[PDB]
Image (cartoon, coloured by chain):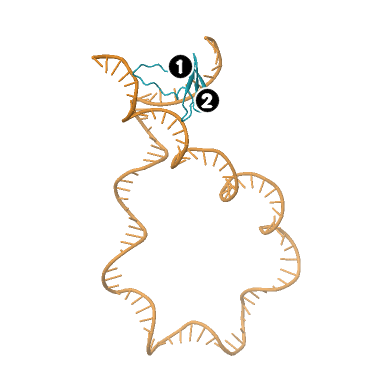
Amino acid sequence: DHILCFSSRGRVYSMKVYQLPEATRGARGRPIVNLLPLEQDERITAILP
DNA sequence: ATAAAATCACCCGCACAGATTTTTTAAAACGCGCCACGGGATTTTTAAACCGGTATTTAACGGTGTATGAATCCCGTTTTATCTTCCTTTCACTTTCTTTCTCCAGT
């Protein structure tokens, strides 16, 4: 499924779910700045499948 | 995949020309000293100027017949102005090594 990510400054980005990193309960994940060209303090606040 | 054409390192002995490397030698220098020489003040002697006069010796002058000085044309020689260059240098970039930070599976 496609997901639309809305940033803290009004931007919209597109991605597919399986491109997200896979991990277990003990892990903490990976930073999202690698996946999307975000700004210095821009953050994601909404996702729409 | 078939044709055309090219290039370099080392080993083994021996003789000699050229390039460092010690080694010896003659010139230049320094310190100390003494006596050979030149300055200063008398005696002595002689070189040259001056009067003669005479007896030569030179230079200026008038004809002939050359040898050379200035001018021209070249070509090897050396100077000077004018190009390219390799090492020194840093320096921003890139790469590569070393330490650290987590993940994380296992018990």
Residue B28 appears left or right of A43:
left
Mark 2 closeness class: few <14, some 14–19, many ≥20 residues within 10 Å: few
Query: Chain letter of disc 2?
Result: A
Q: Position of residue A48 (x, y in %)?
A: 49, 18
Measure the alpha-carbon separation of dots 1 and 2: 20 Å
Query: Chain letter of disc 1?
Result: A
As drawn, B70 above or below B41: above
Residue marked by disc 1: A19
Looking at the rendered structure, the kind of residue marked 2 is Arg
As drawn, A11 above or below B76: above
**In front: label 1 or label 2:** 2
Q: Tell me how many marks there are.
A: 2
As drawn, B83 above or below B105: below
Q: Colour of chain A?
A: cyan
User: For the point 52% across and 25% down, which residue is it?
Assistant: A11
Which circle marks residue A11 in the picture? 2
Q: Are marks 1 and 2 in contact (CB under 8 Å)?
A: no
Residue B106 appears left or right of A36:
left
Q: Position of residue B96 (x, y in %)?
A: 38, 28
Looking at the rendered structure, the kind of residue marked 1 is Gln
Q: Position of residue A35 (x, y in %)?
A: 46, 22
Q: Position of residue B42 (x, y in %)?
A: 37, 90
Task: Give the chain coloured orange.
Answer: B
Is residue B45 or residue B24 the one in the foreground? Answer: B24
Marks 1 and 2 on same chain: yes
Is residue B62 or residue B106 the one in the foreground? Answer: B106
User: For the point 45% across and 16% down, which residue is it?
Assistant: A19
